[PDB]
Image (cartoon, rainbow, N blue to C red):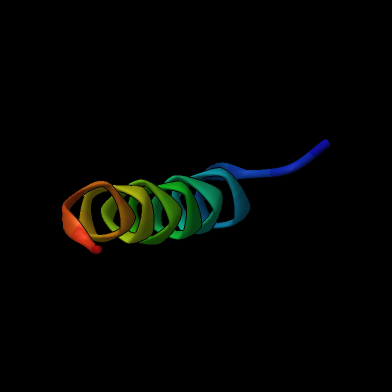
Length: 28
């Protein structure tokens, strides 16, 4: 099963996506 490295990397990717969304929400 995915270890801490892979799971933490996925949380990092999720953080990038969520920040992506934050930016989109402000865009016009």
